[PDB]
Image (spheres, coloured by chain):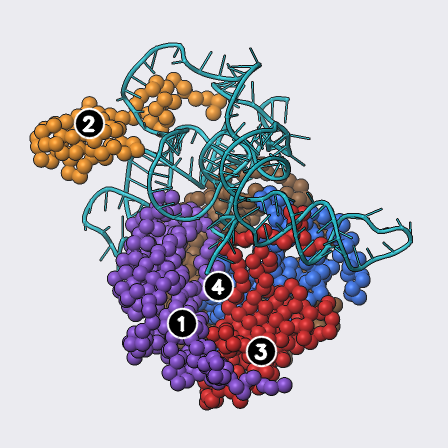
Chain colours: A brown, B blue, C purple, D red, E orange, F cyan
Amino acid sequence: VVADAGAFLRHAALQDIGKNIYTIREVVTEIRDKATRRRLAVLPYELRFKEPLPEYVRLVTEFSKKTGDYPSLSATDIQVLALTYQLEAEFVGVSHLKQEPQKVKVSSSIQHPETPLHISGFHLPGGWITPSNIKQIQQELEVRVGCLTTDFAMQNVLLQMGLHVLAVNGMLIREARSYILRCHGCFKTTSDMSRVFCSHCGNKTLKKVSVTVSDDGTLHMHFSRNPKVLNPRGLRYSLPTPKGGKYAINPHLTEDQRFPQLRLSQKARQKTNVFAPDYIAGVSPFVENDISSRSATLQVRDSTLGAGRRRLNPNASRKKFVKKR
Amino acid sequence: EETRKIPVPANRYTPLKENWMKIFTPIVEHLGLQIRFNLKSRNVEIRTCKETKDVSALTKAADFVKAFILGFQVEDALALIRLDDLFLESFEITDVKPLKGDHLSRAIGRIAGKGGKTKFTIENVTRTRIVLADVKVHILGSFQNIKMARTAICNLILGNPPSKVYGNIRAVASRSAD
Amino acid sequence: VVDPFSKKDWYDVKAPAMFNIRNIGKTLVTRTQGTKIASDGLKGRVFEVSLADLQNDEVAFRKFKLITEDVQGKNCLTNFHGMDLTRDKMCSMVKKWQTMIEAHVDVKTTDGYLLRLFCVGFTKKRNNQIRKTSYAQHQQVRQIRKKMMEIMTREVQTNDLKEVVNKLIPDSIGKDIEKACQSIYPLHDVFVRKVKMLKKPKFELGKLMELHG
Amino acid sequence: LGPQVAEGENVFGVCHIFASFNDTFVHVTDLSGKETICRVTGGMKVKADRDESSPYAAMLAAQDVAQRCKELGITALHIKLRATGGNRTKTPGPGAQSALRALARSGMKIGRIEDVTPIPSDSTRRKGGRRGRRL
Amino acid sequence: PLAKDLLHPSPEEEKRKHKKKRLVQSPNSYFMDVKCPGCYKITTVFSHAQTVVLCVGCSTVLCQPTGGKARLTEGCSFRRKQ
RNA sequence: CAAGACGGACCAGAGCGAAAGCAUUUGCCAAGAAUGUUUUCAUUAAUCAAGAACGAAAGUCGGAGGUUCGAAGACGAUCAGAUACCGUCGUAGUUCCGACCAUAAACGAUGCCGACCGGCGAUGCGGCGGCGUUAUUCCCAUGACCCGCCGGGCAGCUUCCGG
Ligand SMILES: [Zn+2]
């Protein structure tokens, strides 16, 4: 039972199920949540820290660089993989696990990548969210040593090698489906769903492609055969001359380019909380807006705000009295 | 069992999807209601169940999702599931003055102000949330606060400059035992 | 001082046999006071009943207006008087970047009912379309509208009221119009939006018994 | 006094809540709409013209009509919300919202909510001038 | 820009340009030899014909006028002449 | 049931027109830009004193009509001095038909015609080239989409062209 930091984040109190509860010091010392650290000082201390012998750390690295998951994982994730590999080696025979992982098979379909399949509340033609389902909805849910890995790249390389992986649910996981991003310029895949520029070529060209791995060791990857996805409509537009100084917003063309700091005031990026027990004594139903700072005058916005505006293509007609900051 | 259905327009589908967990968690936890999103009919469907604590929880959930779909922040409509004297009155801009074209456009502009400042300042005085859909104005707050907000907004879209409206709205707030 | 609800009486109002659910509900009438009868006080009451309250499997945005036409001893036999969409559905279908195509026909059934049919359709954005707007041209709109009138008039003038109202429950006319208009401009959400009574025939008793059972 | 129905099936009425810009009406009636059961406007509760339109008077009227319905035996209500319409404002005020909320609170089963407001196809001239209206 | 052989444009460049805006004007039309499926008679039809050209020995329509190029009837064959 | 009005949402920096202007279906009537053309005439053209046609709203003469709104006007409220604001009512008007009137922030506060001087992709119409998807896998052309080009349009963005 090797606990990833996802188990500690999720407060998965599964120490009673297993007895081989082991983990790295690095994964538990990197957590920045206060409630998790408070919960760490309360829990019964049966977990033990170790560091794997570095030889299996190499071996895990040479097949992760072959399975297409090496840029996605962290060093600590390689530590978790090496620790569960060594605990498998010490407890169970080593002939069970296989190397040189199997080639992916390709099968495309017609659905758009943004089709909201596998989102809980949604229903095409019953699928309801009951008070009985909230504890149930975690992920796709289906002997001595297991894992508590929630990142998909972890489960991908584990089920590729053949280690039995389990979840916050006690029963082990048989099937794992998710989404990845693939570049249509250099065809290199990333398991990080947040990232918008490619790791290899650096272009803003990653598009969503679904994957599913079995417990057997098979990875099969579903494309979308929809011509909407690969269409260059608003991709060529003329760009302004590059501007410097404290207030310049260049159009963000490379991943590691340097922006001037334009942060919101602490008053502006505060949202109203109504579940607080001191809310009803508060004067207003809502937090006051910031209209007094310098960033209010400079019209600084939250980075997440104004997203559907960006997906409108620049060579198009906006209304005649609006201005796009 | 009784249910309500709340429509979603096409510009409110993606906000409904990103903010979905923040919608269905307080409805099902603190009110104990069933909820789904019918994609074929494009309706948010809210249904009573065995675990509902009391009557008029489902009306609270309906007002919550309605305020979200009109364009309010999810936190400002969690204010609807919590509080009892919060309503929403809306009107078109041409319900006050017949405006056509660029005049109408300027009306929207001088509701909002530069950077949105005017809007925010009105929200700071009347303690309301205003949302300006395409030609339409929606206010959220208490009853007397909503009528103060309408007075300020209607003065803005029958011509008066924002400075006059600022002074009038602060004076009216002072005389209202605020 | 005197309560007038003691003098009132409760009657059952019932849907005809064309819908699954019969008992659409209850109805007050002040009793007979010699001069005016309790019967003719309720001879012309119109009921806005949604379709989900008449059949279980159908959709609830449609409303049938049923007019009561006889009373049979705490039963009120009702006949079809109209249909319209829910205004929420009407508000939801009118989106911006598309063409609204409306049409209307004054069509007479075989048994003497003169009806006015209104049909609305919307141009459909295609599955690989990138252009924001989905407008039809004026000749395409006229062709679509002409075929809409043709389909409705051909679908009503050859049938009696019972068959027509049985094809207004699932909107067979709508599916026919969606299929037939694809060769001009593909259509998105067509419905017979409204059905009116322009003319009724002379009242008969055996006809209502046929429509009821 | 009322219908002779078992405890299972509900006897529906139709509730016309009309939220004017000076008061609010509550008209419970038959499914046909022809004969009326109860109607309590906002001014039947507050003895001041200023608060005819408040959500408080709307709440009180909702309690009154709900009480009268349990007197005569109506258990469930369909609701038709309404504002003035025509040339004037189309969206119902907080009076109709408060009446709906408090009436749902007071033991009524609620059926379908429908907005029957007079939207014109195309309108006559507005009561205001060209110069504007509402202060 | 600032260096362009105006004298010898590429044939792609000339074929793109409007028929007047070429270095020397040249039409985009042609006289095509049409061949009726029934008879053996060779006929010449202008590619942007405006009339309904009839067969001399069959009285069969060959092409219909359109906004631009005349559309040939189904079954007729043709070759562009010289 | 009737009367007179008005054609919302769809409706856009979309279209059309010389401008004022123009949005319910259908039919008739005569016009019109653009595009296409290896058609015809062959300088017939540009800009225009004088002179003419059209010209929002309001207004004025005759007839018809009056639903809504509503200058004048009547009231009610309001004050050291209020005679405008506000509410209810309401006349001419607002609608039509025939005459007049010829003015607007009648605006791009920007004559018209011709030429040259950077880039870009959206859109409206017409034309051309081309894989594919669709008309329940369309049997052929054809419409709806998709990719590029050309021409005249309504606009936009970008630029240290030069002013
Ligand atoms: Zn790449």
Q: Which residue is mark 1?
A: C66
| SS state under label 3 | strand
Q: Which residue is mark 4?
A: C88
Residue D116 at x, y = what percent? 52, 65
Residue type at mark 4 is Asp
Q: Residue at x 59, y 51 (%)?
A: D125
Front residue (pair A189, A99): A189
Q: Which of labels 3 and 2 is toward the front? A: 3
| SS state under label 1 | strand
Question: Mark 3–mark 4 contact, CB under 8 Å?
Answer: no
Marks 1/2: CA distance? 67 Å
Work out whether disc 4 and disc 1 sit on a shared chain.
yes
Label 1, residues with CA under 10 Å away: few <14, some 14-19, many ≥20: many
Marks 3/4: CA distance? 27 Å
Residue type at mark 1 is Leu
> What is the count of numbered marks?
4
